[PDB]
Amino acid sequence: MKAIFVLNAQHDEAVDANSLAEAKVLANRELDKYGVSDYYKNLINNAKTVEGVKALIDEILAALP
Image (cartoon, rainbow, N blue to C red; front, side):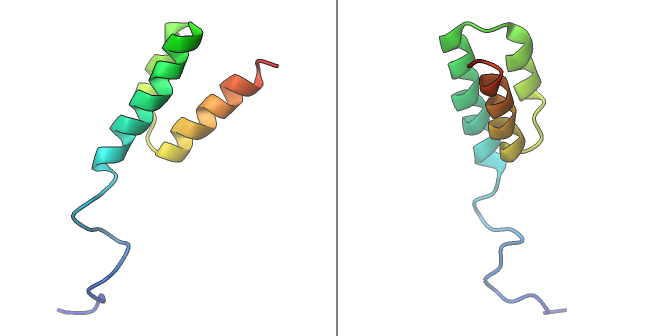
């Protein structure tokens, strides 16, 4: 049944498990720091990927010149 090389990026002991939390926690505090609405922080909680978390703030911060 062997087919995938031992070293691979498919999965490992460390996974996105401990990443969305820090990503959401680091992005969420900035909202609280700025004092924006709580609707945006709730939306981050529903983020399905870090790129979605960082890219969502970029759109929100961009709308603030």
